[PDB]
Image (tube, rainbow over all chains, first blue to last red; front, side):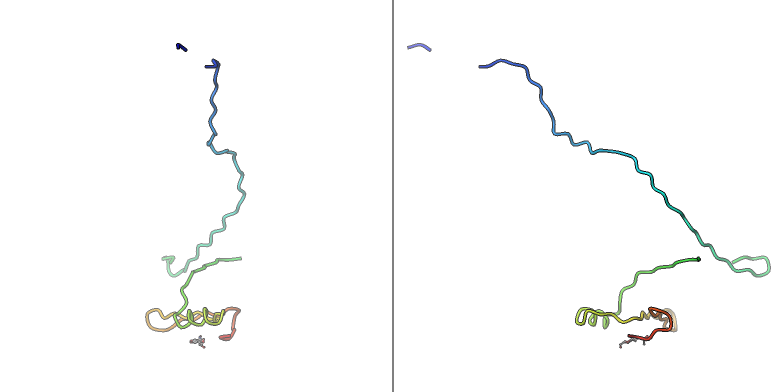
Amino acid sequence: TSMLDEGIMVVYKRNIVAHTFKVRVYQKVLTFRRSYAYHRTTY
Amino acid sequence: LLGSNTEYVAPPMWEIHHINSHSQCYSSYSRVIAGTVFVAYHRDSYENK
Ligand SMILES: *[C@@H]1O[C@H](CO)[C@@H](O)[C@H](O)[C@H]1NC(C)=O
């Protein structure tokens, strides 16, 4: 007593590259130096 | 408007014990450096409430 579909395949990832976008940051920088004064040698 | 030093400091151990047994802190920090002790108060001229 003697005695399989075929096709075309496209595979896809889950994508992991996190989304970039630029951001504008507005801010001010106040700096306070302080000094002493005697003769000609500022401390 | 002028400067703004801000330093972060560990309480004294007697105060640690107060904090976590009463849920409250004293309105004064004191640390000795070199000779004398220094001390800060919350609003100016305040007491040790
Ligand atoms: C504040 O009170 C605590 C205990 O009541 C005391 O140990 C501390 O030295 C006081 N701080 C002062 C008087 O600056």
